[PDB]
Picture 1 (spheres, each protein chain N blue to C red):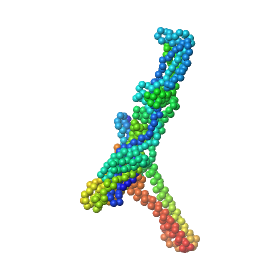
Picture 2 (cartoon, one colour):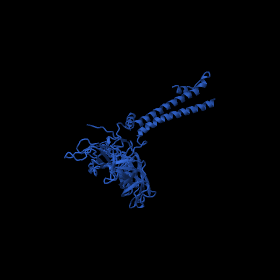
Picture 3 (cartoon, rainbow over the protein chains, first blue to last red):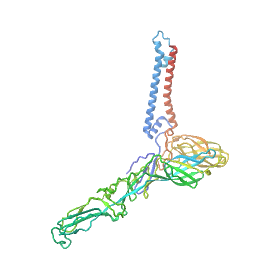
Picture 4 (spheres, each protein chain N blue to C red):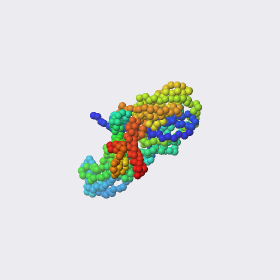
Amino acid sequence: TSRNFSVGREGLEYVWGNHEPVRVWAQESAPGDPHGWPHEIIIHYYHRHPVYTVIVLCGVALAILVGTASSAACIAKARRDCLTPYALAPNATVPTALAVLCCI
Amino acid sequence: FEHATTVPNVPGIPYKALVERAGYAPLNLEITVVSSELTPSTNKEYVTCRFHTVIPSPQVKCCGSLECKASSKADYTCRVFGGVYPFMWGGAQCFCDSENTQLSEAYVEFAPDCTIDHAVALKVHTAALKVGLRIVYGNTTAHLDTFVNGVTPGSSRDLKVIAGPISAAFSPFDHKVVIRKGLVYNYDFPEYGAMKPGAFGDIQASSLDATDIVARTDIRLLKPSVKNIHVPYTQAVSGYEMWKNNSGRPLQETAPFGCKIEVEPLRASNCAYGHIPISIDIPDAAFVRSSESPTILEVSCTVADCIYSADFGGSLTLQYKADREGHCPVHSHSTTAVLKEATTHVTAVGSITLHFSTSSPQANFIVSLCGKKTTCNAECKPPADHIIGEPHKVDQEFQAAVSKTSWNWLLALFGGASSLIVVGLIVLVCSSMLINTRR
């Protein structure tokens, strides 16, 4: 027959019949490349440590999301501040730099 | 000069350090935990084995009267039966066939084969850890057995060392243990005097030869039925045999941290857990002044194909120019890299190769040669082999186990959000200032 035994970094020890104990330790030989493209890096560090990897990826996602949201809110508030005085007044001879910057 | 460090309690893996005095050449200091012994203090509660149910020969007084007396035997049982009229070989052993009283008697003792086949019940206490250490400093090596408690010192003829306490206390033995032909079990045997039939410890004694044997086997005699002389009884099974059948695996195959349980005395050997804080009073004669050691005028490091594995994966080369021929001690100042060598011969000009084991994706660590440092920078690939037959000699860290490419990507992505928030705040502030100016 055949028996599968998971071996961690701390290691494993097995005795088969009357033979002496045999000890084996697991490597960090995950499939991927820490110094390659991002997909390889995430594959490597997810196979090594799935929970920690998922945590850092979700943290990065939250960071980019809140950064984009804050930037959007700030540009919208700047548009409000620099436009509402002119929208309440006639003949808004606006230098188009502000609008062209903050319309998109 | 006294040097204090915190070694990892892992047998067979050298731990290296470089003790640096104010005005003496740096000295190597390498420590190995050759063996350890986590031994508790045990007291014998009792011994037990299969009981031999000895049945004294019955007696008959068959028109008198007999009363059951009390004895001091183990599980002594006595009864008085009436009309029996026993036959032996002639068909009659009695006169006054009625009122025929007979005394049934039975008790238990230790079986003749119990001097080998027996179990001993012990209660353990706080375990004391003792380590055999090999310490080499400079050129001198010393072996010493020291108690890991923080007070008791180890001494080798000029060298004093004090170790302990262990960072995290641990003991594989529960409060109550049983030993049986060198096999130890963490079984909750009954306390002495509280025998129960059909379970372990049903028969107890202070020793194999002890005459104060006490037992409770639920032996009960029965009234004889057939005419011929005999004594019938029924008794529970041997609790020792039942425990043997349901003993389960011993602690030799169940102790965590992979450590060998040995007997006479009870102990656990070569048992890796925690860290040992060790301070060594290095003798003054060991050190030599820096004026005698060969200072290296310059040196440059280049790392060869490196690999972060348990064994000595990577290799590097120091190209050096010095002023004299000597015996420089080499060290790695990073906690995530350990060299193979400790002292290397050095010439006026040349190059020397050093092997090393690292647990980080990149070799970005400092190497010291006769004190002077060099920043070895390189990248290490993942190991090819999945399993090895050797323990990892370097612990894994968090900030050092992430590759510098991944660090750069994460830093850029986080700095994007940081840049976005700061530009938002500054544009808001400048808009506020401008509207204030033009209000």
